[PDB]
Length: 112
Length: 61
Length: 127
Image (cartoon, rainbow over all chains, first blue to last red; front, side, top):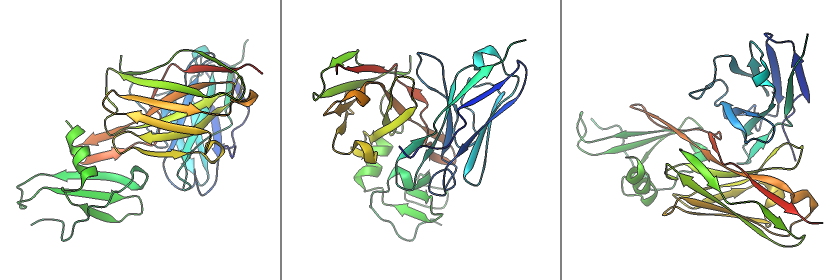
C-alpha cells in the first residue's frame, strides 16, 4: 500500500541511456543500502538486476547500473535495446521490518 | 590472543546482521570464535553453544 | 535447474482459502529466507510476507496479517503460503522468492533482495 514512488513510464530511442528514480523515506530507501532492482517481462516472473544499491548478479549486463542519494535510488540502462522493454521495480527493506516495492516503471523503446 | 572477552547465546535476527565471521582454532586463539557485525555498527561475539548458531554452521558446508 | 518450483494454477470461490506450495529444486533452503510476493493483473509487485526456514521465523506485511500464514518444511525444502477470506482483489499471480547470502574468507553477508523467483501461481477468485 505504502509503495515507493517511481515514474509510471520512461522511454527513449534505441542506443540511448535512461534513468529510473525510486523515492522512499528515511525509514526505507533512506535508511540503508538494502535497495534492489527488478526487471519483469510480460507474462514472466521478475528478475533481479541490482542488489545492495549498485551490485550486479552474474549474468546481468554492465549496461544496468544503480546509485542512491538520500531517500532516492536510481537505475540506469545504457545502450537501450528492444530486450530492455519491460517493467522495472525497485525494492527496499524497512525499519518496520517489511519489504516495500516501487509502483513500477514501464520502459519503452521508441521507433524511427 | 582471542578477539572475544564475552559471549552471548541470544538469537540475532537476519535483519540486524551485516556480517558473520567464523574463526577456527589456532592463529593465536585456542577456541572457535563467531563474531557478528551488527547493522547498528556494534560487534557481538556469539557462543558456539547457541542452537541457532549450531544450525547455521551445520548447513554452511 | 537451481530454482523454486511452485504448485499449479488454482480457481477458488470468494470466501474460500488457498494454500500455495514452493519446493526448492537443485538446492536447499539452507540459511536463506523465502518471501511471498503477489501481483494483481496489470498491477505492481506486493510483498506479503516471509520466513527463514532454518529458524521458523516469519514476518508479514500489515495488510496481510491474519489472512496469511507462511510455513516451511526444511527437511523437504518446501515453503507454503495459505491465504484465507479470498475476494476480487486477491485474484493475482503469487510468487515465492529466495533472499540469498554472500560468502568470502571475510565472512557471511546476508542480501536483502530476491535472486531466485518461482514460476508463479495464478489464483483466480470466481466473483
